[PDB]
Length: 341
Ligand SMILES: Nc1nc2[nH]cnc2c(=S)[nH]1
Image (tube, rainbow, N blue to C red):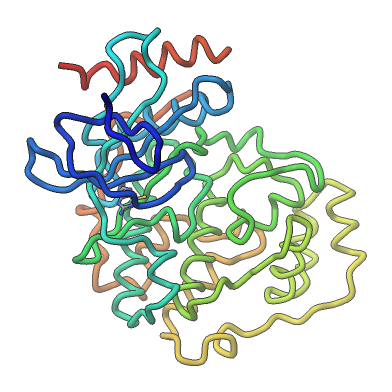
């Protein structure tokens, strides 16, 4: 008989005992557990994707990307538990370092010092530099995907929605795309972008920085179509030059149809913020994604000078250079084989 949690099978033993329900995540039930080999408590995520192709896609991305990546600011996969055979495999359990909290939970009740904001931002960008160097876009950066342990080591998690960057095929039509989580979604997603360029991730980091400064999301759209209203309400009307970069007529004419809006100065929105932090914020939350600061520039920004050290900001050895659910299950089975005894 497998272990049960909340009346649901959570079959991780015998290596992992003393289970404690933590909650529900994007993939399902999450528990903590005692790792009897490493004598430490761990996090375990139960995934049940095999009945749906799209679930299999996300699960395969998550596993394949995290197994290849090795970086201090990216969550590792310590172990993967599943049945010994493909026909017996229904659930997959991903084992990771237990982390005290995440930035979403933290920002609910804790004010961050400028020193913490600086340190968190540095770690996010250090992790992102590695991700982008692997030719990968995370595409769902937000506070709840930033894990923190008791000593404020930050690790980026959930690569289920990630893609290989494809800037030459990024252009699309107006109001069609569905990339990232709404509050953290770049303006071009609603205008003319499929979210296949690294600048998508930098926008999200900008949103996260703003949220660290005030403990409130900076662009709280109430639904998909509301999000652009909030972004433009703060950035103001885009310039002629930036509009000229949008060739799509529906997108450009939508923007031209709007009354003028003034830029709201960052120092009025954040009167207690470090001036260097606001300068960097402005560069990450730049409307035109071609003008938007890139991850290596952001690391070199004066705000982060106490931490900046390119030789200690490693890149990926093996970038990613480039199906029915049954084939995906087979790939998930193969991808997880290394953890079997
Ligand atoms: N507490 C906690 N620790 C983790 N380690 C990897 N993911 C997690 C989650 S979702 N929660």
